Image 1: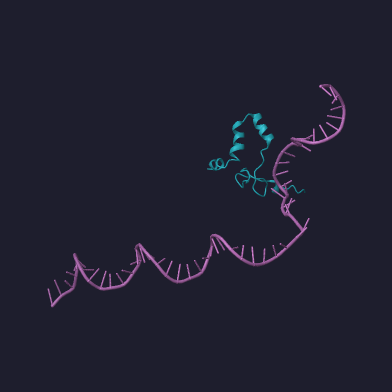
Image 2: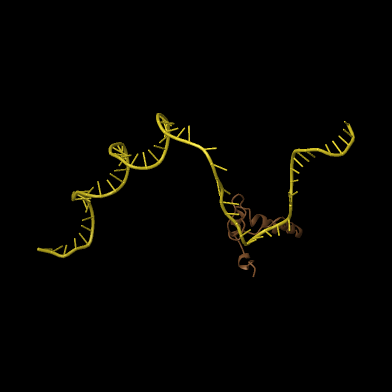
Length: 73
DNA sequence: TGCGACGGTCTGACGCTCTACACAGTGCCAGGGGGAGATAAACGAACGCTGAACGCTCCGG
């Protein structure tokens, strides 16, 4: 029985702590952080040609000090 | 000037979380200027006391 237990791997977030130097969410399981949407993910969404989902994953769901609160409202 | 070569300069070196941590050897005091806190007083205000005074229902001889 390996120590890759499912109780430690599982992590989820809708809205939690945010970073300070830039207002994106921070990372990690213990600090309620969000998954990283890297460059290759953004390439995949451009290859689909989904401008709106990419825009909301880059501007709404992070990095906007006023958009996040308005979207939650 | 053409030649290699000599050299410095410069760049990145797939992706994520589960995990994830903190940081270490040599001086010393006196004189003087400001503002923080405690003090006792002060000019003005309104806060009370004085019941008085106006007016009412009143039980009444």
